[PDB]
Image (cartoon, chains in turn green, yellow, cyan, blue):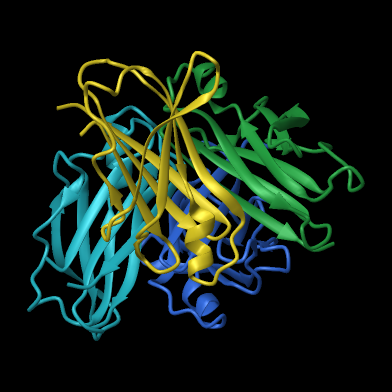
Length: 116
Length: 116
Length: 116
Length: 116
């Protein structure tokens, strides 16, 4: 699994379930091209976004729709979404875990990068 | 001053000095128009970005060039930049402090919204 | 002022006001002696804890009563309190800012150490 | 697994390996009694600290020896250790995951609490 996203809720102490995630790749034109999307599971995780063959060198953006998450719990949050932008695989293929820790007015994001 | 940005370095326990910050406002196009920019001071802060008159309701993006900051220190970082996207609403008088705590593979951002 | 404490609420996007803070210094016993205390102001800050003369090298503990803060807001929190334990060293003149960002099931703490 | 600890390194983007963890339980005397200890694995995780039968209601402290971790990498960090203090199982047995995200001058901690 070359790309995995994990989302946690810091108000409830729980995984953040059914959060929409969109992944984009920067194209040769410098536009953001849609690459993959999905929703987190009951464990807060999103697996199966891509394969090693399709996940080439490039600049990628992971967009986490935090606003819809908090609104469905009755909270009006600060941010419109959380965005993570990074260069991937530029020294060969790697495995990436992108984690986000969500509060209404704050978020933290961490990347764990491992060499398979 | 309705909008202030503060950037901190979690590796060195210091303000993050001379970090470039770009602020964008969402246009009718759905495109991001330049709005304000500057470099953080010795205290890690950026003041003077805008005025009460010009800072109307809308969606704003604050982009922090974190990759250039780490490269100056000789540290290879994960993120291309840190982005904070939010709506400004007139709900009484509002001042916005956007803070970012930087590490090479992680960042935290917090918004403090207060009322004079 | 060699030591300042700042506490922020990530649920409400505000300073955390009237939070009790206790500071301890490590004794020869290996025991924690009361050193200073106070309640955070409307800005979430606590100033005036000590003086350059009394703040000698040592190991210090800063205890923030986060559980009482959340209970006042009607939120059931995870932690009994937040603790920050550190050594102070004379390595030139040092000022310490200890910041805590509070959520019900998470907190972040940062130290900014600067030199006048 | 009623209690699991996960430690990540925000400077290197990796699990924090071979970090010492000590767990204490507050005794009837109000002293901290040793409860369990171990070292994180190559995945940054520490499993097998306790069993459901032994993990009774109480106040627990998880102490993560961050200082030794950073010193072995050549960094002189701010904190002596990271401490997490919490009431456990007071409404029946729960499963607890305690995560810590480490930088030299900052750390974040999160708890995920699930009902088996």
